[PDB]
Length: 110
Ligand SMILES: CNC(=O)CN(CC(c1ccccc1)c1ccccc1)C(=O)c1cc(C)c(=O)n(C)c1
Image (tube, rainbow, N blue to C red; front, side):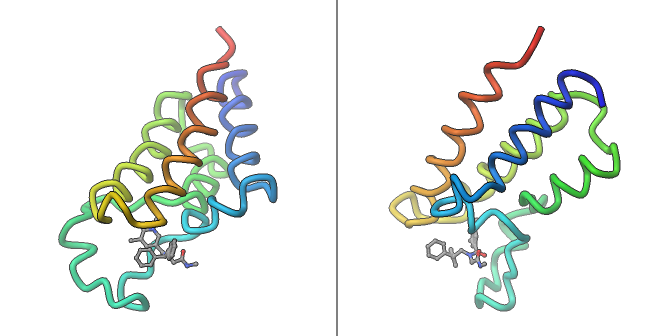
């Protein structure tokens, strides 16, 4: 409800919008490790994060400030960079969506 959290909510809506769906879709929901046969995922990634979890936390007023919101969005990208080989298509899509995030996050009102 704070001005900075309104900015964060706007960014979240954009990341979930059809505008970015071509590269955002792998980040919409938690990685289903069992479904994908990624039996090492939860051994390598101790704190999973995804946009549906960020959305639930925003709706529940879990985030007290913009910094806490940004930490979860960057955790989501960091998990992807940690688990996947750097030449995987999902890493290319992470880099593109993080570019969208970082450039708009940088326009935070003071
Ligand atoms: C709706 N279903 C999905 O989102 C499937 N996916 C992505 C899916 C995939 C990527 C890697 C391994 C196994 C499937 C993939 C394949 C082709 C190109 C782009 C992504 C995931 O769950 C996934 C898996 C991992 C490890 C990850 O870091 N992220 C961010 C998402």
